[PDB]
Length: 164
Image (tube, rainbow, N blue to C red; front, side, top):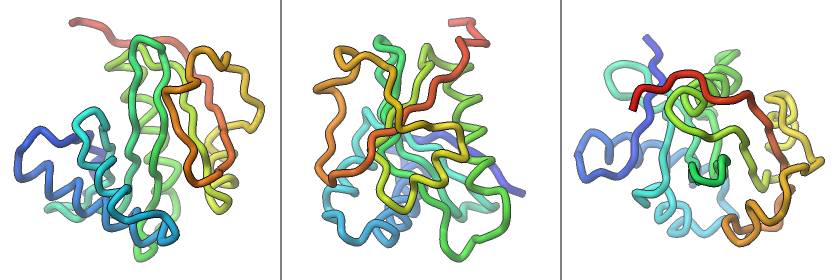
């Protein structure tokens, strides 16, 4: 009943529908952030989004991230589970699925995020740490921190699946 789907703005209606439902969750959960800024990032084609979907197409949460495949890391820009979908497990399963996805479809081995105060606890639970060990030369300039959050890092294992 619950699907974890990766989408991005490739000009298709179904993808836009998911991106929009996700954007609305982020906008509601991060009200102090400029809503148009959130929209721009989610709809940016370079940004991918893993959405938690309940059939038919009900977005219950998700993560919008910016992968830098060549540098082996991705910035987790937005993360949230709908406040009306407080069923235990969604947040953890969403992160678990994203880790499995990037490890099997890319050369991404690290996650970096400027966590908002209220997300720090969740991220720690997902194995992220405030102790940044990824050299600044790798990510500096590639990720921004306009909200003054807390940089956190997750270091994952090397790529699994590879065909093309």
